[PDB]
Image 1 (cartoon, helix red, strand yellow):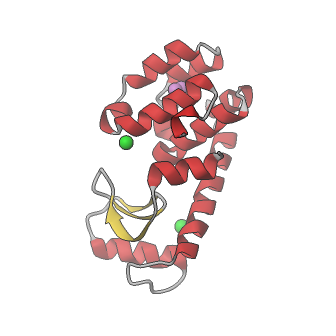
Image 2 (cartoon, protein in one colour):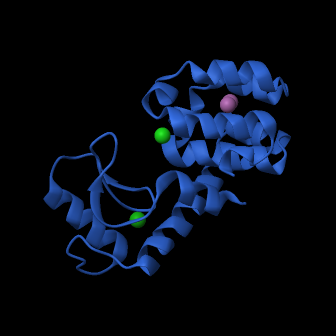
Length: 162
Ligand SMILES: [Ar]
Ligand SMILES: [Ar]
Ligand SMILES: [Cl-]
Ligand SMILES: [Cl-]
């Protein structure tokens, strides 16, 4: 199991523009196109992303490319984020994946707000931080996912993904 497999499991893969649980235009493996309501807006952003007139549809290949970019950017974001970096560097590799998962899903910012869990996580207090992260709009909105991620973080194993 690795970050790619894990997120491919959490985000799925759609070749057509779709709405996320939030109602936002998205495509591929969790690639947010836009927050705007304009589906037209969404196609433009999709065309710009891909480099051609997709007309709202992409190939598998294309989706995997956006995905590759998205993970990479997620990683680089953490590494340049200051609340973030130190936590990440303190972690073992499974747990680092969990953090990347969160950042991909919610952005540096949203991940920034787990200050209290995250400090607990810097302190290696698996149990507490986990219960703390659970009290979040994130968990209440996508509980199954959240649960897999918090288990991975707490445990340092991929059990939740088996
Ligand atoms: Ar956390
Ligand atoms: Ar967590
Ligand atoms: Cl892009
Ligand atoms: Cl979920």
